[PDB]
Amino acid sequence: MEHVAFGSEDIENTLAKMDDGQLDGLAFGAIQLDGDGNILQYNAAEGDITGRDPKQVIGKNFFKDVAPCTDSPEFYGKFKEGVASGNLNTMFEYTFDYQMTPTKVKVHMKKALSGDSYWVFVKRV
Ligand SMILES: *C(=O)/C=C/c1ccc(O)cc1
């Protein structure tokens, strides 16, 4: 297993070195989005939590296609405020309930070290 703790202060530096295969060794869900919300990376732990097949969601828009329950001021609204500002670091609890059993999770959104990319980390609560 890859040893990185959910919510670590330097998580973006640690994950910058990770290929899709190493991202799959994380103890929590990790999704990398571009500024428009398109999925660039989606790890195995995230698929375990949500039921989505990782390879199938890459390239889809997270807010429009995959996760409509997140299209709200409380999730997507925070993401879009962060992209526009060029800075994002927020953690909050949320319930995923689209085409799945309602599941309570802790979400951490953070701007990646890379230019136009943002991370969404997820763990069960
Ligand atoms: C609500 O529509 C949430 C859906 C969802 C959350 C996280 C995922 O990775 C996939 C779908």
Image (cartoon, rainbow, N blue to C red):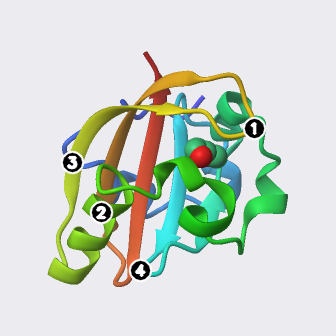
**Which residue is label 1 attached to?**
99
Work out whether 88 lies above or below 70.
below
Q: Is 62 in front, or is 30?
A: 62
Separation of residues labelled 1 and 4 (CA atoms): 25 Å
- The numbered mark at residue 77 is 2
Instruction: Indicate whether 117 appears above or below 15.
Output: below
Q: Secondary structure at mark 2?
A: helix
Residue 16 left/right relative to 91: right
User: Disc 4 and disc 3: Cα gap in Å?
Assistant: 16 Å
The type of residue carrying mark 1 is: Gln
Q: Are marks 1 and 4 in contact (CB under 8 Å)?
A: no
Q: Outermost residue, top direction? A: 125
Q: Amino acid at mark 3?
A: Thr
Residue drawn 22% across the image and 82% down it: 84
Crowding at dot 1, Cα within 10 Å, few <14 / some 14-19 / many 20+, comes out as: few
Amino acid on which disc 2 is placed: Gly
